[PDB]
Image (cartoon, rainbow, N blue to C red; front, top):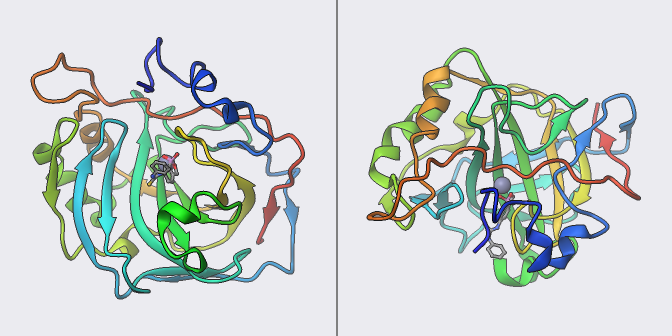
Length: 256
Ligand SMILES: [O][B+]1([O])O[C]C2=C1[C]=C([N]C(=S)[N]C1=[C][C]=[C][C]=[C]1)[C]=[C]2
Ligand SMILES: [Zn+2]
């Protein structure tokens, strides 16, 4: 099936998922000089204090840390959002080299990786229903730049040996996602899509201006993961990012 190889990568996805050539595809390049400051945009409201992480898993495309979303424990509200969006999971996209890895770019600059905190609009009842709606998901995107280590990220890095291959999972309770946020919540926002098949156009993207810093060792360990399943030929999980797509008829708004 789909992947990030030369034979099944982003340039091939449109054959099975024609929406790949849609009107509101992600990611996109964020041109800082063209983004429109919108004084009407409200501050984001990230309430993760009651977050309940459950487990971490390697699904062959990235590693996902899942949360209990059967109640309004960890939610995202405010900003450009109407309503309450519940955190269901987070994952990253990264590169084979420090100079690439993020999906969104800023004035064409690529970061070493990009964290996606995925949330779904509770008015739709469940995640499956939400992805069929234009305002079904709110993904908070955060860039990672290589520099000093991110203490909060280390708990995730240390458990990766236990989910090296596709289909492996491990218990991952009591993880606090607040440890993954930068100091500032200034952001850019635009309507887009999942950056992976089915590439549904159901996402309100909220991308933070301020990157978090992670050490070269932390991202290096991301690169030791495998796309393949155990017992299959080893393919390192790197460059699991889709390149910037045409902005088309959309405006990127800035909260600052
Ligand atoms: O492209 B992404 O990596 O970036 C942001 C993001 C990504 C993937 C998903 N999708 C998830 S969690 N499940 C899913 C599975 C099947 C159909 C629809 C959705 C959600 C958010
Ligand atoms: Zn993602």
